[PDB]
Image (tube, rainbow over all chains, first blue to last red):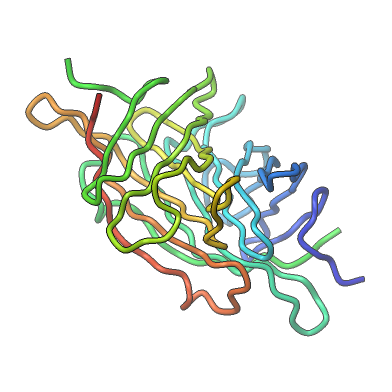
Length: 119
Length: 119
């Protein structure tokens, strides 16, 4: 079943990391959790809180990499959009990572992730 | 004393737009408002909702461009870091803007803003 952009939806990226969207309130404010599974990365396998916004098919979400088990001294923010291609829902995003203690915008890391529907 | 990343701190960028940080809770989760004053832009002069995170000197914040007076059908996300120059606090950021209904990450707009302390 094609998954739409809703509360209680999960999405897995090319690293195997999952965004678990928990609530989307009447204003479109988002809560959820993120589990990182990128091979060799720190802060894997434990849930990090997420907040953000949904506006139709546009979405932003952000996670601070500090939880009860591990810190990675940074914050990731994703901007992107929902699309249905090949009969499956996905969230295509660009992201920025800012590290605590930075002194230059050149230190902000940039990339892109695509998150496919998952159960 | 230079303003730090605290609850009830305000920051104005090069276009005259202001981030009004309301709360920063014990986990560093942020709430606030944003007023856009960029010349020639839509969604000026009214408050938009903000959420995000603070981690030491790292900060992310994001606003959905919908309120009770005007929609701009999009979401902006800023990623940045705090610096203290000459006793002025400021936040150096890179931002991404995603529009509802987008179909390619090439449609996400990007720029650079520095938000400096204001009273």
